[PDB]
Amino acid sequence: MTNQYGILFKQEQAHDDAIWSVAWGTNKKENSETVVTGSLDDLVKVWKWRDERLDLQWSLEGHQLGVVSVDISHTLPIAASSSLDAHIRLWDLENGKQIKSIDAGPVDAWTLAFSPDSQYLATGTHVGKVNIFGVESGKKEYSLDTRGKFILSIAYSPDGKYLASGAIDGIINIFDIATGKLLHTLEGHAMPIRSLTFSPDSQLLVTASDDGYIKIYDVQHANLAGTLSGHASWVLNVAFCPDDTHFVSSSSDKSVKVWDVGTRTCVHTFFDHQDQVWGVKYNGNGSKIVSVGDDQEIHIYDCPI
Amino acid sequence: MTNQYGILFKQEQAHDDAIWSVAWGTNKKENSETVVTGSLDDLVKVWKWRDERLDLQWSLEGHQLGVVSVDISHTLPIAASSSLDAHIRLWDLENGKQIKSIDAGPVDAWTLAFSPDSQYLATGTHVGKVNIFGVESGKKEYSLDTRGKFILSIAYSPDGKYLASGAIDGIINIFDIATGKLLHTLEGHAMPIRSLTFSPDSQLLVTASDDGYIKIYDVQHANLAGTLSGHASWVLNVAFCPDDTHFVSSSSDKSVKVWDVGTRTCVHTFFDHQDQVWGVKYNGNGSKIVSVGDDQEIHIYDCPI
Amino acid sequence: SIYSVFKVAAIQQILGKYKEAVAQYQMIIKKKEDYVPALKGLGECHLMMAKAALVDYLDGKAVDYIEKALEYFTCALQHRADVSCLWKLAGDACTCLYAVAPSKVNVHVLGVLLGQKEGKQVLKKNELLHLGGRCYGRALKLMSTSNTWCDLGINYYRQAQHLAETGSNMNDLKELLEKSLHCLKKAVRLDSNNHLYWNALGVVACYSGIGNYALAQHCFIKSIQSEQINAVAWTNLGVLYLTNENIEQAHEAFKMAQSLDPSYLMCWIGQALIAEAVGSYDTMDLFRHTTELNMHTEGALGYAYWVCTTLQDKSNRETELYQYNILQMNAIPAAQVILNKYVERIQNYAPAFTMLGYLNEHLQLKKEAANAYQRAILLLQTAEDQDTYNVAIRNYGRLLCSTGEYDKAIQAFKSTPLEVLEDIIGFALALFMKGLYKESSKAYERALSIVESEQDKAHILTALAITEYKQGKTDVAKTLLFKCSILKEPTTESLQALCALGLAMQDATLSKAALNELLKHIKHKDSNYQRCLLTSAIYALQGRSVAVQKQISKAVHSNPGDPALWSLLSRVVAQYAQRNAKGGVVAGNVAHILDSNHGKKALLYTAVNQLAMGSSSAEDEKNTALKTIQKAALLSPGDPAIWAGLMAACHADDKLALVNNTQPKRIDLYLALLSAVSASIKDEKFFENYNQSLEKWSLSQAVTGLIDTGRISEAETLCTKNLKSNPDQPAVILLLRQVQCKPLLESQKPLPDAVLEELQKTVMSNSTSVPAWQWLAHVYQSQGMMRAAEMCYRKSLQLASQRGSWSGKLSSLLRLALLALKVCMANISNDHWPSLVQEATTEALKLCFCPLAVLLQALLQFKRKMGARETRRLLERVVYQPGYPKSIASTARWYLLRHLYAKDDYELIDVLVNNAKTHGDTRALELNQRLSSQ
Amino acid sequence: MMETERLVLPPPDPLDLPLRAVELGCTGHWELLNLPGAPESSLPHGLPPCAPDLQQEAEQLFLSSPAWLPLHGVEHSARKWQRKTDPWSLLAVLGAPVPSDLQAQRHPTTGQILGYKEVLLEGGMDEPTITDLNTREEAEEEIDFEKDLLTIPPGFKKGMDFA
């Protein structure tokens, strides 16, 4: 019953150090398939999967410390990255030379996330707020406030009007873009979350925590649909499939597992990635899976519909 | 029936802290009687028993943390030592000045054991493998791999072609040097072993465990010949006599006992060593017994043939 | 044409994908707003999605879907009011929301339905059921069919059930029951060949208010006969037999029904009920399978009760039933989710709330536990209140006190009769937590008077000593702990408290006795970390500072596992005896390897050890202090020490890049890191002295880095703001002086003796710090005062030697040697500076093996002489013996080549030239060629 | 101390180069730069504070409060609950399917849709007082449910009997 799964591509050494983030973006209407990775360095190398392999195209740089998170937009060709250098400089992604550069410390911005219309590029700060900047318009026009500890994750629904945020100690806050008032706060876990993502036609919110558990919550209320516990170590990143039937999770036990929401079970497990895996993402259509690990290797998988 | 036993020599304070390992080597054909000890320091002091006493000859040092294991060769004059410093530096033992220095952490090497021809110097790691280096030739040419926990004991048969290894939780693995393939695994105990030794014309394997029991196994099969339980505390080191008639075991209850393999009973017990004893060894011929304890004292005994 | 697109959308609806069909129907309704079939399709789709949502436990989604379906249904009924399809669907929609959380269902129904057309109105559950009955009656009037008769009967049954459930009335529902019975009999008599009608008749007959079991059995048998594969009727008969003490035949009927349908939940629940009633061994497994299948309330409650009972019993810990059941299946989280759904559905069971609270408490979910206890309190005030309510009060108070909110916890423990040990002890703990130690002490003696279960008494004595000590007055607490020790069997907590109390004073002998007592006869404790920490603190208190490493190495050797011990070793070598920096780095790396959740502290400690070491490696990347501190920062960006280490690593990397002379990098981030340090410091409970030291070090290092990089204005503004915030402290005034004196004196300029005197007075203001003395000696040297700089260096040396420091002594020695050698190089008379050089270098060589000191000796000797062969021998020894830094070897090579060119030996000059060529150098070869062409 | 300034010659000499030293780390490791200037010492102020000392740590581990004692633990309460079961919630009822599909009509010849009429499958619209009274109006089979009732279930030898 379990479908046939195959890698079809393994990269020997993409970078020189641990890879911390990866983003796959099918931004343009034709087959672009742009992949941007950042790995404990100034290097924000951009790869391209042309037919069956990855070919390096850009080696744009200009950072001073290790980049911790990268993200890519689906409407316009653009990219953004942040590091411990306290600088959010967004690249052009076609010629790749430093369109802008925003000053914001670890007390002002931690992770990156583009708006569904690629207009705001919200970030999270130490004091618990969620700083929202403006692309091409200005810096720090306003920020939604919640009363909590260090905030790590910022997630956007694929239709807007929602904004989730995970924080240290497990407290989860949900805001509405239309008004900006705190709707309801979810207690969540007792350990840091460090991973959130919505789904299309959003009605499900999936949380990954530091204790190994995976909670399945329901938006617009506080009802949880279940708890998935299959991993043995910390869970670091979770990405959802383009159709609401599966989602992939990567843990700290050197194992990448894919679950199914309909039956709440693990359909397959991949035994690769000899070291920790720090990022997994889907492509435009749910056929391939990318995964970058603490060890210097980039893995692409194949998941049939 | 029990023979006359006497100490004939007691050292007041050989070192300043607890002694963790001892090696007795009759390397040269004439009366050398070299004794090397390491004791919770940088000091790897080498003593010599000339006629009736021990005389200090070398006080070579150069370690940063406590030395946990020492060994001496019987063919060539040479010595080796390892510590928590993550350095296996082998000494000349004639002039005693740092012939070599190999980099290997506690995750790469824990204990030392010379080859019967003094050529391989196998060690044990946390991940379960058995790293084998090369004296005078190179570093880390190959390592036998087993899927287990921290490994503690490494033993060589006096004719080669065999390699035993005790580990935490009691799992015992036996390898053959000629090929390097796992022959058979013995369940043993459920707690760490921390002591192993073969016998001449090797056909008997004696194991010491943490629960006070002493198992006597037979190589080339999985048949156990019996279980000896006479001690009251942890058993730390076991050394076998040059003739297959006796073997000496040292426990944590401040008692040194000598057993006999033929009838599996304790012929005599020595009530000395007010604190724990961490090492016992035999000399070239089975006439004297050395024992080092947690208290700073060196004891030499006398066992008639 | 629109009919084709509508039929396409209808087909799309049949083959699932209901959302697309709803969107298509909306698109069709866009062009034409009065098409009836599209409204009917939307209503049917909304009803089915609502029922699917009700299959799971989503009451808000279901209520919203019913409201939308009702709006669409009345919109369609506006246009065509003679169609039995719309009337029956409206009745179905109204009666569908049955047995769903009363007082949570409030639906907006608009317009004609509620008599006269008036805006929008809000109806309750009973009113909604009455409207459904009316709609069913209208459908029956327009079309008389047995199906609608049965639907009306089921609606009346639901109305009667709702009226009975809430306890609103009794014996006044007989008319409704008679109507339902008549409708169902009429329906079954219109067509007596439908198992559905027969089963419905049986179900309505067997209601507790009627209890006509003979007719129920007849109807169930008839339904079975009408159609053979009837699992529902079979399991209904099995349930009837089971409740009327018929275990055997109920088991037979449930087994047959299970065989006829393997995926039916009620038959499985019945099997579980019989197994529980007989006391079998697989009841828990049956309940778990039932809960996994379809999340029903009965299986939920059974599984919850069994798990709670198994957890409550404390003698099962190794029986292999508790182990497998509660660890291999991960029972606790599944039970927790099950209880949230059950309490959402029912929400009037205080025991269920208490079980949910107990599981959440066990799972460290204290806020949810407090909420559950609050709901149980609200439900339980109007109860018998003997055991349920007082226990609820105590548990609510304990949980509330645990999550702060101390005043409310005190009030909650006030609102209960204080005659039981649990309530008094919880009140005492909350009282102590807020403060107000005297009433807490009275309550604790009261608990001691009541106490039994002597271990508890010993713990009460320990608590009394702790709270009494918080009030000072240590002698009586010491006597109390001694009294606890004299008792027949001491407890580990009491001995640990006694040892820590002895540690608080500087006595150090009572602590040794208590530690000996703990070591003598206590072995069941399975925490090596606490004992090792206590022993290390014992040794460190007497100021030895060396036996700590020996004790921790012994502990690590005894237990090679326990990564906590490795982390402690790394931390201790970071703090005490920081000469085994390589060993500390190794211990940190090993501690990080052995596990994952210790990586933060392990990486911090190995980063600090690497920083202390410097650059004593093979110049390999990916293994420097910067990389490890970045990894630690990623793992846990919450502590201030990581940011401080980041500052130190950035400064060290700046110095290394200057030394290698390639590029400065990571220039200006000190302000952001300082702000992060302050923000992360502000959120810790109490480390007052440690926090003050951390902030002082961070601020001073940031100011120094800004001064070094060249942002003099920002540093001055920061210093002025700091001095304005609070009254003056000498360290900040010295820091401001250093900031101010950067513009003046980089380039040669004389300064008044007045400025020197205030600076000297300020340096005197904050004494016992070697850096300030060394800096003032450097300032004196820069203006030029050889004697003053030498006296200041001697003062710093004596200060460092007295305080037990070692790096400061070496630095003072080397600086004094450099100064004296510099003044000697000016070829001045009064040749006492060479004597100073010789004494300083001899002392440095006695301290350790210093290549810089031997090079200074060689340079002075070279200044003195040149004819003597020995000078050449010494220089060749320095330049040729291995294990030397590149710069010192280069300087020795340079001076040797100079001396030999003066001595005119071309073979030796060629030897030096080729030796320089084997390594990497340019300056020596350049000067070699330059003097070759004289 | 005299406080006599001592002027040193301004040019070092080209033939000889200045002596600029740099200190690396706490554990002694020096070197020599070519370029005359600051002593340029790394971590001037010492190592940073790191973790607190062991005495404070042990003071904090125990003498913070009595909340770490096992008398305020998850155990030591001896709770217990009382089991209630409810077989009757295992009854199930199904709903009859809709009796009409509302199928379209067609003009005979040149098929076109005139309207929609309700086909069977195989005044004052406010629903006032719509209840049904004066029952027992038609004859369907005249079945009797009150006199002769089944007792024997199918497949089963005898049946449980109620008075």
Image (tube, coloured by chain):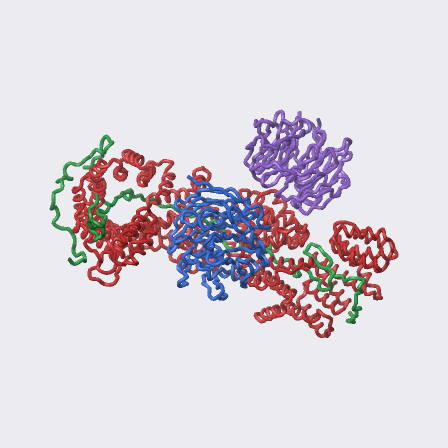
Chain colours: A blue, B purple, C red, D green
Quadrant location of residue B266?
Answer: top right
Q: In this orientation, does residue C118 appear?
A: yes
Q: Residue furthest front?
A: D110
Of C62 and B217, nearer the camera is C62
The number of numbered discs placed on residues in the rendered structure image is: 0
Of C888 and A33, nearer the camera is A33
Q: In this orientation, does residue C501 appear?
A: no
Q: Quadrant of the C terminus of chain D?
A: top left
C206 shown above or below B197: below
Quadrant location of residue B252?
Answer: top right
| Residue C500 placement (x, y as % from top left) | 56, 52
Position of A288 with respect to D32 (left or right) is left
Q: Quadrant of the N terminus of chain D?
A: bottom right
B167 shown above or below B3: below
| Residue C14 placement (x, y as % from top left) | 30, 47
| Residue C256 placement (x, y as % from top left) | 29, 34
B4 shown above or below C889: above
Of C674 and B94, nearer the camera is C674
| Residue C512 placement (x, y as % from top left) | 61, 49
Position of B24 with respect to A3 (left or right) is right
Position of B220 with respect to C908 (left or right) is left
